[PDB]
Image 1 (cartoon, protein in one colour):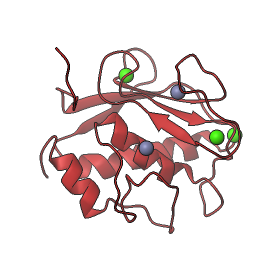
Image 2 (image 1 turned 30 degrees about the vertical axis):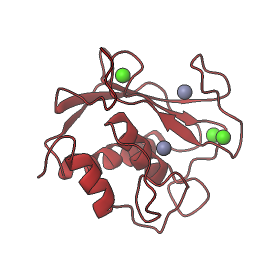
Image 3 (image 1 turned 90 degrees about the horizontal axis):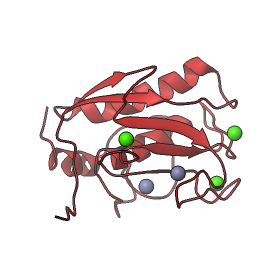
Image 4 (image 1 turned 90 degrees about the vertical axis):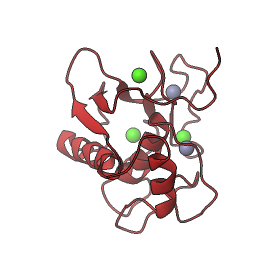
Length: 162
Ligand SMILES: [Ca+2]
Ligand SMILES: [Ca+2]
Ligand SMILES: [Ca+2]
Ligand SMILES: [Zn+2]
Ligand SMILES: [Zn+2]
């Protein structure tokens, strides 16, 4: 049996930040992430819970180069991050390119921004064409980060509304 549009069967997800980036203070990273998950669960029946150890549906880690999977990182620039669609094991997980410089401001590569998009993948969404959507594959940022009606239509189509 092959599923083409996998989704989480539980609207009650647990995530875990496996390791941190030296680029930013632990509380900042913790904020950018919990606040990227906030975007998604507001417009759906999704419940996210942080977990420091144990089982986590979504594992988050900052890594670099070849990190075991088959989507190695290219050093500075190029890809900045990538996530896996809903599924067992590595599915739902998000890996950020440690070679990038992660900021909490307008400088190149704001973590919250990139994180909101990768989390869209862990929840089952794919890329958008609409350049004003969070799911658009190119890095953009204007101070505030919110879901576009596009991301909202895409995500509710899978789980439901709020
Ligand atoms: Ca997982
Ligand atoms: Ca890179
Ligand atoms: Ca770094
Ligand atoms: Zn990876
Ligand atoms: Zn993407």
